[PDB]
Structure formats: C-alpha cells, structure tokens
Amino acid sequence: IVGGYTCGANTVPYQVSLNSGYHFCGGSLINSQWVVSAAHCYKSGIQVRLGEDNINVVEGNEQFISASKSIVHPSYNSNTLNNDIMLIKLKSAASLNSRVASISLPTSCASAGTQCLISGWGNTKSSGTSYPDVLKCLKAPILSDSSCKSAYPGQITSNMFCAGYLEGGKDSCQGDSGGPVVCSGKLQGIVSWGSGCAQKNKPGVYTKVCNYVSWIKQTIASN
Image (cartoon, rainbow, N blue to C red; front, side, top):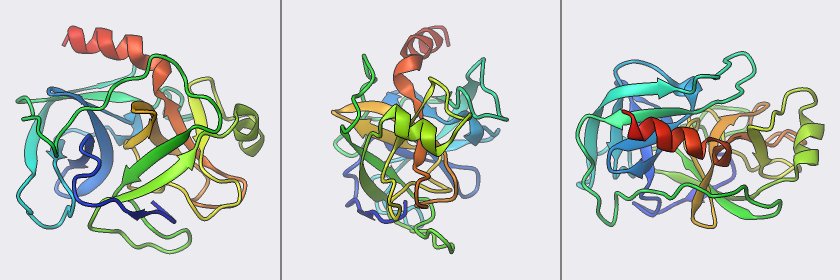
C-alpha cells in the first residue's frame, strides 16, 4: 500500500496473509472454511495466516492453517487478468473471534464515489521498494467506469473496476495482490493489477467481486 496508514493490530480481521515460506499475497476470509484471493496469486503449498498484524513476529493472535484445495476461476485468463479470482479452502476451520472474522459478500455493485478500505502488506513506495511488517490501510473511492476505461483503454472488462486517486500517490501495490477492497461492509474488490503503483492517471484495478457471488456460493457448497 502506497500513501496509506498503519491500520492498527487486528482492525481488519478478515485480512489474511498467504504464506509459502514468506508472505506473497493477501486474501479475505469469507467463512470459517474459505478464503477468497486473486487467481494470479495461485501456487501450491499455501499456508493461510489469520489474525496477523506484524507478519514477522508472533504476537499471539495468529492462526496458521494449511490450504486443503485451491480453485481458480474457470475463466481466469492470465494474459488479461480477466476473472482474477480464486478460492482457498482451509484444512481445518478457523476459530472466529474479534481478531479473526469473515467479511460479507456483496449483493450488488457499489456506486462510483463510495469509500472503500484497501489493505495489505505490499510495497509502500511508488518508485523504490520497502515492505512493511505491519498491515497497511488505504481509504479510496470507487472511480467511475469511464475514468477507469479512459486510464486503461482496451484492457478493462466488466469483471474489473478502478478505485483510488487519478492524481497519484495513493494505491495498492505488489504484495497487496489478492487482498480486500471493502465498501459499506462488503467485499467489493480483490487487489488485481495496475500500472506501477500510485502513478498519475493509472489507478488500481480490482476484481469485481459482485459478478462472482453465484460462482463463489456454488463452488463452496460443492467443495
């Protein structure tokens, strides 16, 4: 997260870290057994880390649970990042508490201008590299689809939306991928892609979760 703020320990209790010997992506707990992330975060041997603040220090509220299965969206296209969504099942159910909590799925899209919370452990610099140990947060508004498509001509599908600031300086970044965009108490987005980070007229692009709720519910119920 570039241009954000320190969230505060466990203030985003649905935020998970995906770990394969190191943090590599975020995700969101949607029920005690299931995490949603980005398809481009797929790999084998994922351990889900819940209740994290400092990802480098055991602080006492963590749950580390291996994934039993990963399901990439059937239509995921790694060339265009269309349908950049995947589900991860926990080998054992997470223990829900004040610091480990699920985030509700949306019933409809969110309007342009709605304020959202984006979070993750990704790079905090727009030109250099500096990775934080504690969770970072950003309030960012949903941008109009027209401004999103104007910024990325030929590359935005109906399964993507933009959020952030056209003036630059505030954006998600590498290492935030797969993490949440939450608006009005619902998981509206997944950190997906963008042109650099926090650059002018190149806002963050996010998977449009509301388009996938039917697939999420059917897939979880069958797996």
